[PDB]
Image (tube, rainbow, N blue to C red):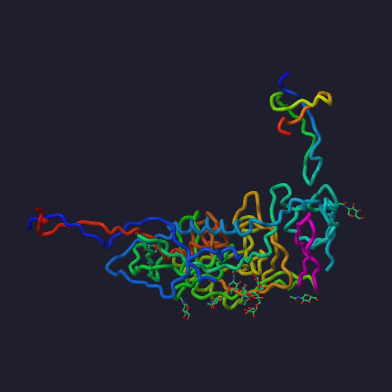
């Protein structure tokens, strides 16, 4: 061969997988995710295809879901830091049934003029927020009394999800898998480089994925391993299913004095009949959606297998479907969607809630005045396998489930991978440097 | 005697489940109240 000599090159387009922090970006305008500090979005972002190069994607290793997990919780706690403690409101409640029982009409006597202007301030309380005192009437008190000090969320904080974007830092790039058939992992062929991702709204829910993206012209079902009962099945829907939710009760609210310079909002009277929360779901769209899902499930789980039975498994907040329409947390019985194996949902409202899990300090929602209405659609859902059974293709009871809230972002992040680019490299050449 | 066996009565149900909860205390952690029995309290008071 030729006498070869070392030549140094810079700008070499090669890279290695790496994990780092992506910068937030937002369509700039006390909403939790509406941080005062965030990069304005690019009105004309670029995307280029590699084509000579493929890349190994694995949605179960995208560490970006961890960044979102921690940052989102931090933002929640920060916005709701200067909020009102319920500590002096642990006073026992003399409760009777509210005439029309999920709502009790109770009284108490605290603080009784501890350098302030206060009184008994009777009010309405929800069953799901209190603990019975079986040694009394039965009487009630705040369920938090024997656990922790919790605060009433600041009335000035909105909880509307914001579609936050995330962009690569210098020296790093975001690769995207554009294969319509891409599942949990593999050598994605259609790979492109993206300057910055689209916005993902931090929607928090249990059992069904709401207001997300749609599948590429068919239902696509993903899992780490369809044979492993310890894994979950992620279903991305071809078209979404329409759901319309309402809180028909027109509620008032009252500010009460709890100390000098301190106020607390209580549920006031209710105007009109007291009715149940519920959501209306189109059976047509729901059933047709299931048809496509079943067809795909057959590919792995058998051609005559009975699927989709009633809700079961986990504590009440896992067994019920959960969402936060209007700022109030609704827990509805999804069984009405899965009450027939191979639509109006009854629903209750809770105010003392836990953002995915909370230790010690927790959030109590304020009462919302008026009526709550919203509209959304089911764009995905999580199925769980019921466990061991006869191998024969008889049953596989894909119950709704999933309590790991991180999957509400992983379900979108699966498209992306972050790498570190190494511009420095060498190769042989023909001649020696003309060294004197 | 370096260890005293003492009682008290606090918080007496300030929205809680409490009682007199007698316990052992060390001499070196308390201050005598020479106007009482002598009785004691936390030296940090
Ligand atoms: C999935 O995505 C959908 C669509 O984004 C969400 O549904 C919407 O949620 C927003 C949340 O704010 C609703 O917006 C509210 O509408 C109220 C009345 O709506 C009428 O009036 C507004 C006036 O601008 C019109 O834009 C609208 O079209 C209607 O004509 C407003 O009164 C609300 O503002 C008040 O409340 C907020 C509370 O934070 C205050 O800050 C304001 O200052 C003001 O007091 C608010 O704008 C919207 O109506 C919903 N759509 C529908 C059809 O109902 C789903 O919630 C989302 N699902 C999930 C799972 O996230
Ligand atoms: C859909 O998922 C299957 C199962 O994981 C993928 O097939 C495997 O891909 C891995 C990638 O490293 C290979 O090691 C296995 O040998 C593959 N298994 C078989 C039997 O082919 C498949 O590639 C995925 N489809 C897409 C489009 O990503
Ligand atoms: C609640 O009020 C009734 C009013 O007659 C009273 O008899 C009862 O003892 C009260 N309960 C409590 C918790 O004090
Ligand atoms: C996905 O939705 C489109 C909507 O027009 C439909 O035409 C298509 O048939 C659906 N895919 C399957 C697998 O049915
Ligand atoms: C789902 O709801 C959103 C709400 O804005 C709507 O824009 C979208 O078109 C809906 N999806 C379908 C498939 O109708
Ligand atoms: C609730 O009832 C009061 C009664 O006066 C009415 O003024 C108010 O508009 C009602 N609110 C809603 C949202 O219907």
| Magenta residue span | A250-271
- Residue A330 visible, this angle: no
Observer-nearest of A306 and A15: A15
Seen in the image, is A189 located left or right of residue A93? left
Seen in the image, is B16 located left or right of residue A67? right
- Residue A282 visible, this angle: yes
Magenta residue check for A236: no
Seen in the image, is A1 located left or right of residue A363? left
Identify the residue shown where x is 51% and y is 65%.
Answer: A305
Report x, y in % for residue A362: 66, 54
Observer-nearest of A343 and A22: A22
Q: Quadrant of residue B9?
A: top right
Report x, y in % for residue A144: 71, 51
Q: Quadrant of residue A337?
A: bottom right
Identify the residue shown where x is 80% and y is 34%.
Answer: B20
Q: How many callouts does the rendering have?
A: 0
Identify the residue shown where x is 78% and y is 70%.
Answer: A274
Observer-nearest of A218 and A418: A418
Dominant secondary-structure state across the stretch colored magenta: strand
């Amino acid at each position: 061969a030729e006498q070869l000599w070392v030549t140094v090159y810079y700008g070499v387009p090669v890279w290695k997988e790496a994990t780092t922090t992506l910068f937030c970006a937002s369509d700039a305008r006390r909403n939790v995710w509406a941080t005062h500090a965030c990069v304005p979005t690019d009105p004309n972002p670029q995307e280029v295809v590699l084509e000579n190069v493929t890349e190994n994607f694995n949605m179960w290793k995208n560490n970006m879901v961890e960044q979102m997990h921690e940052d989102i919780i931090s933002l929640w706690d920060q916005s709701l830091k200067p909020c009102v403690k319920l500590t002096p409101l642990c006073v026992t409640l003399n409760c009777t049934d509210l005439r029309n029982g999920e709502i009790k009409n109770c009284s108490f006597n605290i603080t009784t003029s501890m350098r302030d202007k206060v009184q008994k301030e009777y009010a309405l309380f929800y069953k799901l927020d209190v603990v019975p005192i079986k040694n009394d009437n039965t009487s009630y008190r705040l369920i938090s009394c024997n656990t922790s000090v919790i605060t009433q969320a600041c009335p000035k904080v909105s909880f509307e999800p914001i579609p936050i974007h995330y962009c690569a830092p210098a020296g790093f790039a975001i690769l995207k898998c554009n294969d319509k058939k891409f599942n949990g992992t593999g050598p994605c062929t259609n790979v492109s480089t993206v300057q910055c991702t689209h916005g993902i709204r931090p929607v928090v829910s249990t059992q069904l994925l709401l207001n997300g993206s749609l599948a590429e012209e068919e239902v696509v079902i993903r899992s780490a391993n369809f044979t492993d009962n310890a894994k979950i099945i992620i279903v991305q829907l071809n078209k979404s299913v329409e759901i319309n939710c309402t809180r028909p009760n027109n509620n008032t609210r009252k500010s009460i004095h709890i100390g000098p310079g301190r106020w607390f909002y209580t549920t006031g009277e209710i105007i009109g009949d007291i009715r149940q929360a519920h959501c209306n779901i189109s059976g047509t769209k729901w059933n047709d959606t299931l048809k496509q899902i079943v067809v795909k499930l057959k590919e792995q789980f058998g051609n005559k297998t009975i699927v989709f039975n009633h809700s079961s498994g986990g504590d009440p907040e896992i067994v019920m479907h959960s969402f936060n329409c209007g700022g109030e947390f609704f827990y509805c019985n999804s069984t009405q969607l899965f009450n027939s194996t191979w639509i109006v949902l009854p629903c209750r409202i809770k105010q003392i809630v836990n953002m995915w899990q909370e230790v010690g300090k927790a959030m109590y929602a304020p009462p919302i005045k008026g009526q709550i209405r919203c509209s959304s659609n089911i764009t995905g859902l999580i199925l769980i396998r019921d466990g061991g059974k006869n191998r024969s293709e008889n049953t596989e009871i894909f119950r709704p489930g999933g309590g790991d809230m991180r999957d509400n972002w992983r379900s979108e992040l699966y498209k992306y991978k972050v790498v570190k680019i190494e511009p420095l490299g060498i190769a042989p050449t023909k001649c020696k440097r003309r060294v004197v």
